[PDB]
Length: 299
Length: 295
Image (cartoon, rainbow over all chains, first blue to last red; front, side):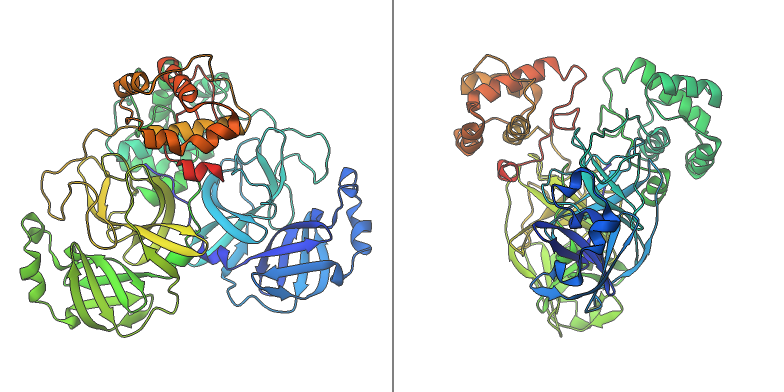
């Protein structure tokens, strides 16, 4: 069962390069605004304890070089929204898709278009970890690359890459500049918290396995939400809520396996392992498919 | 992370092809639409299709080609091996720079999975040693294509034709020649035992050393023959002297001789991971080529 990224064409046509002094990163060009991480205005000296309000008052439009391929876009205004810099430009992007800015929850999934200095390089599907980091690609200049979902012809942008954390994972904001997780855009000591497995996604993936004919892990038992959660916490799994059970309802109806029955199967898999078997061709449980993703893909 | 290529250049080439009651995907490049020739088959025809006989009975107007909301007029048709080539009225204004290439098992590429002309998702994969592809959920994804992009040029290497009984996919290059022993006929054909792409695992281990992970190395070496005798017991592909030569650059970069990395792999197969990960993976990854790894 292969994870897929969304087709990236609609976002490719929005990627540009933003340069401020010695610093270059990626920007997102939608109509006549370019969005990018505000730390593009920072020197290395400023990045130790930057005062962004003061640093931007000292900048003018001529400080910003924006290039869309082989075309310079002239900046005619600049402002900040939280941690995102907004550059008003000469020209509306003729390739702007229908789009929205949305904020996602930990455990939800999206595609990332990894870009280097305005040039799209690759696309991958990922989940926002419960500790609010993204286990991401190995790039050097991918700052400002964005994450998104597509529904019909509408691109929902949910993520912009700002920082690489010492453990090798990525941290960022939504497109309104609000950070995901307890991180700041500063060269200081910060580390990802202890991550956990996304339980509701593992359950969704077990439902996908049942829809695809792999049923060896099903058993006769049921558990309770309370006692499953005690097994979850003991195995570094997120707790399961009544809302999670409700989200899994369509898959329980389709397969005939109640959610607390599937929790019983997962509880046994966590205590006794796979005993040499695989679930979807995998000896490890996967937690980067949401219930929405599985409904979308399977039913 | 295994990344796919940005799919935009291929998205602009996907169309829907309908013949009778059968519909699948086509690839529109310049004034030609490429699609599986079994678009001219019903389900029953697939048991024993005679493609020459089925095709001689068609006119251009039997082929309905839709590019979004625009019908494309077919003005000629021709069969090349297992691919149908529909000449249309209009050259695709979105045609990228492109080439057709035939790949070898072990090579990687991205697939743009499409349903009835509409792009649905993109994934990165490898052509397995048994000439199949582990595919995606979409039922009617026939005609979806696989590709690499190098310097803004799309090299198309794969077109999906057939779903095999175990759930994997089989197909052709863009000249219509199947990969492997498969045919565009519903027979009892099945994927053979798959094996692991050894040269790709070794390239990935080098990537891990280059990125700072060294825990799996040991003090041993191996002969090539002893490595292959062991690796085959784990259903790994044999490693050839070509493969050893290909890894030379990474060997030079890391100061780890190729057969020393082979000795490490032997131990990894014997021991498993013991709870650890190598890059971000709890599994030995075999879908990064040595070309992929250098950058």
